[PDB]
Image (tube, coloured by chain):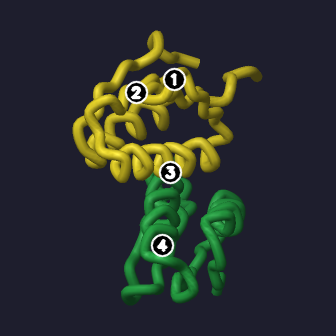
Chain colours: A yellow, B green
Amino acid sequence: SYQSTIVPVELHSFEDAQVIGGAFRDGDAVVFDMSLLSREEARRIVDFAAGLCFALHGKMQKIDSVTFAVVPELSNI
Amino acid sequence: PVELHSFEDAQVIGGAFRDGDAVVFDMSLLSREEARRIVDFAAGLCFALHGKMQKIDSVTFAVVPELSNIS
């Protein structure tokens, strides 16, 4: 299946979750930074991302305190 | 109708919804924080599977899977 190299996303508010969701839903891995978000917002981003991962059997990884990644299930027929 | 007790129940909603079932959940027993975490998780769930979330009232929401239609 098609998938670009990992999509980077710099977050500024919870609404940006949509960018992560869009790319992840379309088969792309996404790494996003939460350096500029409040503690509350960061938490909302991760709960939304966990919802995305559970729904499509994706995997979420923590790179560091402000950097996380969601990776789609491997495409193998 | 799922009665939530903690954020850990997000999996109950998720499992059912992922299996193609509509889920209506009550958040009466949840803290303001937990309630919000549940809805954010559920929103990720719906976004991922092209589902729909509806607010029934302040403590009751529903996530509904995309309708199966083949042409």
The CA span between labels 4 and 2 is 24 Å
Q: CA distance from mark 1 to mark 2?
A: 11 Å
Does label 2 lie on the same chain as label 4?
A: no
* Relative to B16, B52 lies left or right: left
Protein chain holding label 4: B
Expressed as whole percent of the image width and height from the top left, the position of residue B35 reads: 48, 72
Is A55 positioned to the left or the right of B66 in the image? Answer: right
A18 up-or-down from B16: above or below: above
Residue A24: image location, x then y, percent: 48, 32
Circle nearer the N terminus (1, 2): 2
Look at label 1 and name its amino acid: Asp
Residue depicted at x 26% and y 33%: A36
Q: Which mark is residue A47?
A: 3
How far apart in space, not on screen, are marks 1 and 3 (Cα)?
A: 17 Å
Question: Marks 1 and 2: which is nearer the front?
Answer: 1
Disc sitting over residue B35 in the figure: 4
Can residue B20 be seen? no
Q: Which residue is mark 2?
A: A32
